[PDB]
Image: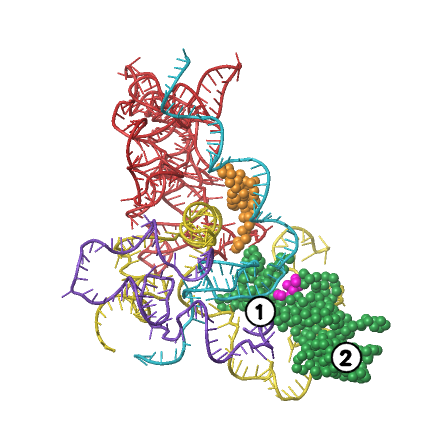
Chain colours: A green, B orange, C cyan, D yellow, E purple, F red
Amino acid sequence: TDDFRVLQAVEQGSRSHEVVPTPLIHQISGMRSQSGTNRAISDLAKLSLISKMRNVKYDGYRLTYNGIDYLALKTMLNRDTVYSVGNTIGVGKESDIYKVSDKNGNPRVMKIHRLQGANWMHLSRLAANKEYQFMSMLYSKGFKVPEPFDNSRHIVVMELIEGYPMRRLRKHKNIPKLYSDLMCFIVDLANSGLIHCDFNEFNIMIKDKLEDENDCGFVVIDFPQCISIQHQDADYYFQRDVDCIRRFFKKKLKYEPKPDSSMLDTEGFGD
Amino acid sequence: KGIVLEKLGIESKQPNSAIRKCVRVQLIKNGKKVTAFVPNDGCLNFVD
RNA sequence: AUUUGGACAAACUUGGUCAUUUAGAGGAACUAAAAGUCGUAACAAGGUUUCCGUAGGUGAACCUGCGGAAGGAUCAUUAAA
RNA sequence: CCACUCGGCACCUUACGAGAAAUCAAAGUCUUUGGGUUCUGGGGGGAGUAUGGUCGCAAGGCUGAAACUUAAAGGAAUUGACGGAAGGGCACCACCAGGAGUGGAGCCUGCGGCUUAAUUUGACGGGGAAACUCACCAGGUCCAGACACAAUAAGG
RNA sequence: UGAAAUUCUUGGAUUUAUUGAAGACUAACUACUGCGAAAGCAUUUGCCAAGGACGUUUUCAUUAAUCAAGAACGAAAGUUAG
RNA sequence: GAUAGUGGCCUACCAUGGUUUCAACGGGUAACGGGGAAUAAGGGUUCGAUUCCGGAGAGGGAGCCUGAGAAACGGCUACCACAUCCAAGGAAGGCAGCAGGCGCGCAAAUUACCCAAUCCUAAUUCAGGGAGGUAGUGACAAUAAAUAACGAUACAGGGCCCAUUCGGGUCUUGUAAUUGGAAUGAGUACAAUGUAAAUACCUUAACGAGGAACAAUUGGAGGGCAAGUCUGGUGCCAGCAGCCGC
């Protein structure tokens, strides 16, 4: 409790100034002697959790990406989250995705964000908060999407979903209803006011419950591509979504549309 | 001269963290309550 | 022995006043090498010409009238040498 | 307009001299310390607060503490280290004109992860590969240890 | 007004022109300055009563300097009564 | 009038004076006044209950007898406050004198000896004196100054000149709980001196040290400020403490 509290205090000793000198980490902690502060900073620096910037007549301490997530783990110790860390499935551009587990033993997904001194951390924070709010907007509207657990300042911990992408999915039996689904869902996107331009094969994720009841769903992860309908180029974005669905269903599922697909002028009488 | 009423664990925090060993006394001549330091005895084993 | 009247005048009582030693009883407030709770702790940050007198409303704070001070960073541009 | 003279408000040099310095023709003639005279201060808070007096319709003014607390609070001058100012290079590990592409399929190969008894070990290691190389496992084994020193002897 | 909303305007606002009333100020000129014990003082003209400096071959002859006590004045704001 | 005696000292009758910013009057004092004490280049600052002089008091007030002299406390009387004995009727009391006890507090001695000094009192050379002197207790201060001094050896050096080399002596160190012969008081004590009697001092027969114990302590060793670049433990009572602190 206590060491994590003092590490939270020097976390709160970051939102005061720029690159923090040694005596501010001495005094913001407010600890007893030279021992705790100096040996803690040395434990940080040897684990690369802190770095020394010595700009003339001026010692200072430079926090890298390492010595933050513990506090996030402490922030997630508060919010009942992950206990065990590490299984690499997917190293993305603006996040690194890991498979983790709680005290309860259910596996979850840990997207750490790495987008120094304040701005790498803070822009990872803005990215995590923005994606968490977009996930909140999608789940509040009712879109079938993974359920968010938390957004530990810059690391998003969410659920794991049993799905595999459509590139390894040959076909299903109810192909025209799947086409009506992947038309009406982009219709629902235009009724939300947004167009997800990367509506590709690798986006769409299908969970598979049974083979008799047919009670399943979908997962759509296109977050840095959703564009409002008011922008300059949304017409052929919508048409690229529709036509990628149609060209995939012609190439893979060998299905041509008997009803005509919706245009942007069709969906202008929507939202 | 006075009569010991209490032993006191006073605390000195900054910048020196130490546990000061003191004694609350009531003086005989006045009826005056005065705290006072007692040196060199970590146990206060000579004082009750 | 006793006794009248005087001045000297110790003391005593009655009140009323301050100045106190107290005891008790009534209340109020300050503290924790005490321990747990909610409020803004585990929350965001924000204001930033600075003051002086006076008046007002205030709120966790502080602002607005009237008049002074600089204890505030004079460039250029006319002439001179 | 020129020249002089008083009496002002200001200016601008210097330093003879002063001062801690900024600065000062007085803030000079002060350790080489004395022209006359009025008032004020004695580290910082507590505090221009408490109480009393006095003045006032009121608001307030004048006068004015102590307990307690503390090693600094200050005045002037000096330097550049967290200035998130703007401007140039000058680069296909940058962009535009493009070309070949990767990430799309299968497979080869390096890392991570899992698994194990070991998947030896680093961040191409000349680390190309059944033996070796092998640095890892399952086992099975030799060979240890000098000199000193008490016994033990050539029929042992 | 960074941005915007209350108010007024078809009986006419705002703006334009001709007038009239009220009370307050005294710009530019205005500094490279002046006066006043300070606070303070910028339109004309007049009245009253002061004042500094200058000049003096006028007068008195120490009447002086600084001032607890005491006394006048004292921006702005604020109190009472027109 | 009263007094020893002037004097509002008091009384009768008259006046309306007297003091004051050159500080009256009131208030405070952990204020007896002075000779003096401590500390300084000078000028000053602060104490003076305390050995000498003067004042005042004998639990608090008051009053008085005697006497030249007292408003006397080791004299009396009354009140106030304490307090003693008692057969309950009465009767005695003042240590801010010398000792000593309680209380109080950081804070302070013996219920000893003596009139031999120094003086004083009396009817007086002789008697008397806790005045005073003497001794005890006494690290209040102050003076003087034991806890060792010489040798020889070696060994290690250093220096002086002769060194051509040895070695020829002069010193001075260091050690070696190595050795030698000396000196003497602390202490004990015949005696004598001392003194009123003693104790102690000054003398002195006889003992009295290698002193591995006739054993010198108190505060320090970052800086101020002389002294550690040393070792161990600590580093959960510890970077800590006139100040700065690492």
What is the chain letter for disc 1? A
The answer to whether mark 1 and mark 2 are in CB contact below 8 A is no
In the image, residue E79 above or below residue C26: below
The answer to whether residue A142 shows anywhere in this view is yes
Give the residue at x 61% y 69%: A121
Which residue is tagged 2? A183
Residue stretch in magenta: A67-75
Read off the residue under disc 1.
A117
Answer left or right for A234 relative to F13: right
Name the residue nearer the viewer: E55 or A237: E55
Does the magenta portion include A271? no
Q: Nearer the viewer, residue A162 or D91?
A: A162
Q: Quadrant of residue E60?
A: bottom left
> x and y percent of residue C48 in the render?
51, 66
Quadrant assignment for the C terminus of chain B: top right
The residue depicted at 63 percent of the width and 72 percent of the height is: A115
Instruction: Choose the circle earlier in sequence order: 1 or 2.
Output: 1
Discs 1/2, front: 2
- Give the class, few, some or many, for how many residues have Cα within 10 Å of label 2's Cα (few <14, many ≥20): some
**Predominant secondary structure in magenta?**
helix
Say which of B35 and F201 sits in front: B35
Circle 2 marks a residue in which chain?
Answer: A
Left or right of D99? Residue F61 is left
Secondary structure under badge 1?
Answer: loop
